Image (cartoon, grey):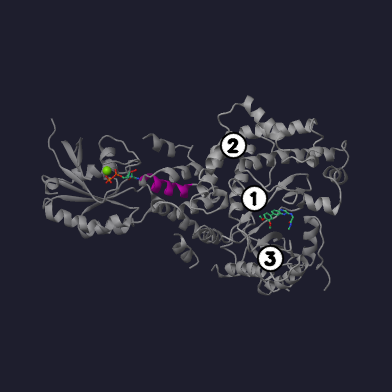
Amino acid sequence: SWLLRLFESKLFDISMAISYLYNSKEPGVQAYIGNRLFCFRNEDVDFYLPQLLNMYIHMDEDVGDAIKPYIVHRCRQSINFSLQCALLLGAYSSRGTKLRKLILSRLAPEREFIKSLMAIGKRLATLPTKEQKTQRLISELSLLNHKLPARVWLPTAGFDHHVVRVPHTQAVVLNSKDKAPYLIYVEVLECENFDTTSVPARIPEDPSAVALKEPWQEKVRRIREGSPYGHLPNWRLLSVIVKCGDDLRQELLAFQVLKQLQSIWEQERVPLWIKPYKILVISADSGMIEPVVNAVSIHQVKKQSQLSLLDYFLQEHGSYTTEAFLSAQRNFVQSCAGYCLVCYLLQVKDRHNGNILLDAEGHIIHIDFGFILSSSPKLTTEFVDVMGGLDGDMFNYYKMLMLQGLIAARKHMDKVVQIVEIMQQGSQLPCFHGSSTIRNLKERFHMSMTEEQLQLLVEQMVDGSM
Amino acid sequence: EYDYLFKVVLIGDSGVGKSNLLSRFTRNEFNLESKSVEFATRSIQVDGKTIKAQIWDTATSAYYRGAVGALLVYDIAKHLTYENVERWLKELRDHADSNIVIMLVGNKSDLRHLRAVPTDEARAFAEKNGLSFIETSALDSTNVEAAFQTILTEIY
Ligand SMILES: Nc1nc2c(ncn2[C@@H]2O[C@H](COP(=O)(O)OP(=O)(O)O)[C@@H](O)[C@H]2O)c(=O)[nH]1
Ligand SMILES: CNC(=O)CNc1cnc2ccc(-c3ccc(OC)c(OC)c3)cc2n1
Ligand SMILES: [Mg+2]
């Protein structure tokens, strides 16, 4: 019984537990794994929730019933976990429909908060301009404060809390599209546990109702001073982008791959920088997003200042001799190389300075992970300059990070491919158009190649990226 | 030499692990992977006596011919297996020896988080029919030998 020696072993984690539960056709093995789930940490299993729930819906019934006991147990404990399941079950369904209707059978206050937000975004289809929508949006969101606080929370927050106030004057529509997305600021009060504390107390000219483009720290202090709940130490401000007409399912998949890639490089001690933003799937056509603070598109940086990338760096950080620019440049190099490997492995397309952000530190951040892998309808000179030319000592450091980054990427390619391979199960997503999408994913790792041949791959990859 | 040769039988819905109980008690081995009539024997000492226990396993009347003890093995992770105990009882009433010691067995007790059968309600059913009760687990050998040790000791 070597197999039992493996499960009994310390080498048995949640990742491999999903591996055997995904391949094994042995009822005794499946039911056993369904029991070991209770032994794992709640946090470690949550990451593979989109995987588990997806296996539950688009696989053999003998597989779903094995996970059901663990899922029900966690739903009975966490109201948030109950919400997460009800959203994922209906989002990937096109079996768990009979389960979603009982989990929701308490969550009334929360569900009402989601429908309201999505409804607000929908009505903004009449206002043809970005300015008109924001005008109606702010007035629309001002109505929500008339029914707060309440048993409502932002799932994107890394803690328990109660939504108390909504600074509508700070909200705004992002673009002039039909079902245009809108960013909102939400004031919340943290707590020990959501399923423990009751809804907090409620408390009600030309002060803080001013909308400016400023840093996070300064935009929170203003909203704080104009907020009735701004005197409690429990107070904290969050922000989420509401998309009432976009499918954030592929966005969720890309997120997991980023976190996995982020861990691998962190465990292999490779100084690569990438910033995965939290995603929340409400349906197969909606969802929210938590935008990273103090970051704007490069296109919006070249436009507001009318400069080059290197110019904005020297102006906002300092001269080449300044230590501040050195750190800012190092953050740029590590962020580029980090996201270059992300674009190659995932095959991220539609890459432009509108989907590429830039934070205060100097890191770059890719967004909009549509057109990845199969789905579909570059190192610009502007970037190469910031690294000190093609023969700059920092550019060679950039090519080195991709090498030892790709090397460490092969040392854990198993854990990464698992994320995408499982999600392809029954999904009608455009990123799974080709019959053999997983094969190209594995071959892009090049396990067969050697390190001597990897450098040639890295070198020939950078050249073609121009 | 061995004193006597008992003939106990293992019945129940397929998948409860009566085939694994047979391997754990005798040869002391358990495998998660499954395969598929068969019997295995192992002699134990009971009251200063040597008894060669002849455990039978299936996948009818010939099965019950010479049957000394009965082991109803149900799964605690599948309530349907506990529901069919009444059907297996009728299976015993019709072909089995009129004076066989039936010891109820709740296997797979290691699946603590997937329990579908209450340990107190199942044990109560053992009192309603005056049958011996015990929950085992062929995976970690919990009360495995104790099960047959009792069923063979109670046969006197
Ligand atoms: N978790 C767990 N699984 C068990 C236990 N006993 C048996 N099994 C599983 O049950 C499955 C079927 O058992 P099997 O030998 O076919 O019993 P049979 O159907 O009555 O012949 C096997 O794959 C075992 O892995 C136990 O105590 N715990
Ligand atoms: C309101 N504009 C800003 O806040 C500028 N700064 C930031 C900072 N982090 C971001 C993270 C994610 C996204 C994002 C991701 C996916 C999207 O759809 C595929 C999307 O389209 C609504 C936006 C934008 C971000 N923008
Ligand atoms: Mg068998």
Near-viewer residue (A420 or A264) = A420
Confirm or deny contact between disc 3 and disc 1 (CB under 8 A).
no
Q: Say which amino acid is labelled 2.
A: Arg
**Quarter containing ligand 2?**
bottom right
| Marked residue nearer the N-terminal end (2 or 1) | 1
According to the image, label 1 marks what residue?
A369
Pick the residue in front: A224 or A288.
Answer: A288
Is residue B4 found left or right of A232 in the rendered image? left
Question: What is the magenta range?
Answer: A28-39
Classify B62 as above or below B51. below
- Residue A136 locus on image (x, y percent): 73, 72
Numbered disc 1: secondary structure? loop
Q: Point out residue A417 in the picture as x, y percentages from the top left corner.
A: 54, 41
**Amino acid type shown at disc 1:** Phe
Magenta residue check for A36:
yes
Within the magenta stretch, is there residue A126?
Answer: no
| Marks 2 & 1 on one chain | yes
Res A269 visible: no
